[PDB]
Each structure stands twice: as structure tokens, then as C-alpha cells.
Image: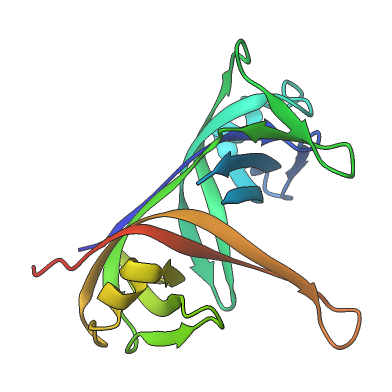
Amino acid sequence: RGLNRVFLIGALATRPDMRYTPAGLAILDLTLAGQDLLREVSWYHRVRLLGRQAEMWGDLLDQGQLVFVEGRLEYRQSELQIRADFLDPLDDRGKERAEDSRGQPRLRAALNQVFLMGNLTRDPELRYTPQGTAVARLGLAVNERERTHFVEVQAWRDLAEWAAELRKGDGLFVIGRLVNDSWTSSSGERRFQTRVEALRLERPTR
């Protein structure tokens, strides 16, 4: 059964970029930044709002603003983007921001949670770090009522060892955090990709 829900709370790293297609569809791209201590983790996630939910916040959001986004992952051949269905500005009373080397704000103790359910597209791939830590990498296919969204899921330690027994075709329920990799290809090609780091895994037997 398909499940694909994203919940994010962070600060706007920069003032959002609003544009319109020739047909009048509003597109609002935002960059949410947050960090937490699980191991200190930080993230910058690009989110896209469309239509009326986008126009609603046009010229109202500035860098630093804390926002809550409810959305979902959307796959395209590849690229996995974060689609915001709704955005809600939040009061920053009692909240603290960190500042990166570029002067951009990141919300401390931010929210980065995703719920996913689908089936494995292949058998799990497990490797061990020099220190002996287990790391599992899974390929997940999430159906939505019809298209399929492919998501790379990574798990650590016990969670990784639990996942190693899974096999292609198995159902998989995941609660995780969105993460991304960024680098420069052989040439100048600036690369970027989004994936999920599992916090909880279950095997639905529907």
C-alpha cells in the first residue's frame, strides 16, 4: 500500500523564488534549513509549492522565517523532489537559529520526518564501515493513486542488519529523515540528490 508523507519545520535559508508558467501556474521554490542532534545532523531541503498555496505566500516570506511544510516526494526520470502541499509560517518565540558559513539561518531542533511505504525494487545491499558498523541501502517503489515514485533508503546499525534479511518484492514501511548528497561531477557538473535515512522500518504483509 502506498504511503508518502513529508513533514518539515525549518528556517528559510534565503528569500523564496516565485515564478509563473506561461499558463499562469504559480511556482514557489523555497529552501528550508534545519539541524538536530541525534550525532549532529544538518540539512538544506528545496521544496516546491504550486498554485493557490504558492500564491498565498508570495511576497510574504523572508529569509529566517520558520515554516511548517506538509508534502510528499515526487519522482521523475532521475530526480526526487520535495513537493509542498501546504506551508504555514510559525512564531519563532523560544526558537533558536544557527548560522552557516554563508550567513544563512538553520533552525536548531528542527523537524525532518517522512513516512513511506512500498515494495523493494531489489535485494538489500549491506556494507560495513572500517569500524564494523553495518549500513544497508534499499531501493523502494511507492505507488500512488497511477504512478510510481522510486526512493533510495539507507539504514544504519541494528536497523541495517534487520533490513539485510529483506528481499526484492518485500513490502517496506519507513519512518525516516530526508537527506541529500551534493558534489561536482568529473566536469563542472554540479550534482545533487535526495534520499531517506530510516529511523524505523517495518515489513507490511498486506
Which residue lies most toward the top here?
93
Q: Residue 6 in the image: x percent, y percent? A: 44, 47
For residue 159, side relative to residue 204 (left or right): right
Q: Residue 7 in the image: x percent, y percent? A: 45, 41
Total numbered circles = 0
Q: Is residue 18 above or below residue 172?
A: above
Question: In the rendered image, which quarter is residue 169 located in?
Answer: bottom left
> Which quarter of the rendering shows the N terminus?
bottom left
Name the residue nearer the viewer: 196 or 48: 196
Indicate how the structure is coloured in the image. rainbow
Q: Residue 198 in the image: x percent, y percent? A: 40, 61
> Which quarter of the rendering shows the C terminus?
bottom left
Query: Residue placed at 34% from the left, 84% from the top?
Result: 121
Which residue lies most toward the front here?
131
Q: Residue 17 in the image: x percent, y percent? A: 78, 40
Name the residue nearer the viewer: 69 or 196: 196
Question: In the rendered image, which quarter is residue 67 located in?
Answer: top right
Name the residue nearer the viewer: 44 or 95: 95
Q: Is residue 49 above or below residue 147?
A: above
Q: Is residue 18 above or below residue 83?
A: above
